[PDB]
Image 1 (spheres, rainbow, N blue to C red):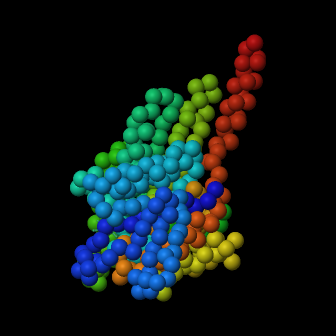
Image 2 (image 1 turned 90 degrees about the horizontal axis):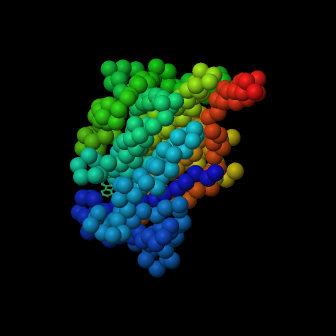
Length: 349
Ligand SMILES: Nc1ncnc2c1ncn2[C@@H]1O[C@H](COP(=O)(O)OP(=O)(O)O)[C@@H](O)[C@H]1O
């Protein structure tokens, strides 16, 4: 399968309104067009994605791409793939202020919740709707920040540790001593998300908002346990769901962001510089390995952001060419069960 790619243009923000910005983004069907406001004579550049989300107006518009609509396209599809037993990844990419955090986290005030809360609510709603007493489940959450190549645990802020990223000699990269907490309700996972969001690194340069240079990775380990009555074997399906709010794409400590660009470019071109940054190392499987992966590229509508928005569209266009190699998590015991059961009914006959 391919990396799925959506782009999303937001309303003007305060900085843009301040400079009487005009809109340089047009969307129709799956295509996004960007005009060059500095060379108005040159022909607009057009790009085709899995989705082009027009969120430039307000939810009063019939044509406004809502939080619900964005979730119901990519978020629901990836949660369904996790239920099938695939590892899944959604990452939000783009310039500072373009709408990565709004898309991934959103706000609680007025159905503004983003992909992460909607997926968590959908996950627990599906688990709690289970009617088969042979199905049992486990949900483990981890939430980390990568800032200047240092890893912090957002679920245990009293660990000023800069957790070490390691390659397991057989099982691939992991964050040594990163909290992995069992959660049994949507309320519990929401409180951890909220607490984790508050522990993110702030910067004076961003008026003491969350640093524009910090990556946030939200991971769920979803374990589905099927109890077989006849055999008493329990089969396990395990899926890792990685929901990523990247550092701002604009332009040592931009190592991760710059390396992600080279990784996307090298994967689109198909050596691969995964290990040159903590982000691309930890997300190696999600960037062309054992994962179903989607990119949501946030776009400023404003003339003043032409060059950065064009760069986001070109990286999004390249991500579309990446192939993944996701396999279903298979318990070998599923075959032992089928055998043991045939062998017994046959004797019983
Ligand atoms: N689709 C959208 N509709 C409405 N407001 C949006 C949308 N996307 C972003 N915003 C708003 O734009 C501003 C910047 O978005 P934000 O998510 O903080 O950007 P980033 O995380 O990319 O730096 C915020 O005030 C946010 O609420």
